[PDB]
Length: 322
Ligand SMILES: OC[C@H]1O[C@H](O[C@H]2O[C@H](CO)[C@@H](O)[C@H](O)[C@H]2O)[C@H](O)[C@@H](O)[C@@H]1O
Image (cartoon, rainbow, N blue to C red; front, side, top):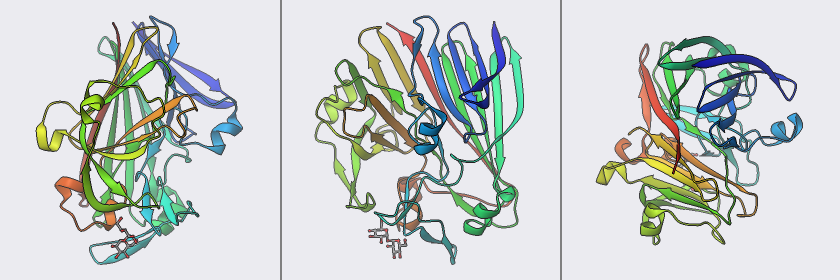
């Protein structure tokens, strides 16, 4: 059995949806952020939720499931594609970067909902051609549609990117998914063997380096004393197997299995100073500053949409009790 229910979340219109296992709340006006995800059998909130509307707007990439299109940093807000130069807003002033794209602070539209014995679906969408300031930076008719499905114990979260315009464009997407993570008693694992060497502006040098603690990382490890803001390379490209981050909550015995498809070639892991009680395992289809790297696309994960084409990038959050 499943349900949809319109609600007000901190004074903004929102949609609660779920079944007997899981319940989400998506907030279309807040960059289509999935702001709440609850495990119903244990009654546990999984995501970092904002105390107030104002605290959300202070840091809208540090709550729920923010959408990063494109993800992370572009040096000087500048890059070229097929001969043409682009200038995105420099919103990270100290490191002189564009950071986190166009969509996490814009209003999306609810395009449909669908309920069957296969689960409950909510779809949201935004058309960048309708955003005049975005068009100044990125004059392309990109349309992004999110399809959220809750079925059994999994939230499926699919992004479909469409080129409805006259020219090709490069694209990447990531999520800044912020889980509650008590440092003392939760464990984290990730399918990664290598990570990208970063400079003081958090920009890749182009070099990869082995993750020294990769065995611990694969198995599940605590993050006490470890401060992360790291760009990991998914091990899937080179080794196969899985592409996923796992969080294990030791008290209620809840496993959160965050899977992503082969397009999600990189994971950024961020836990601030380690004392903020959250963790962001962020799957990205492209590496930070991918647009400015002369490296093969099999590595960077850069993608291009020709006019009239579309691509769906899949990921999912499964909650297991063990
Ligand atoms: O932003 C345009 C420049 O992009 C590249 O350089 C930046 O990105 C590199 C890779 O992350 C950094 O090492 C470098 O420090 C950044 O300045 C490109 O190599 C430059 O030619 C472009 O002007």
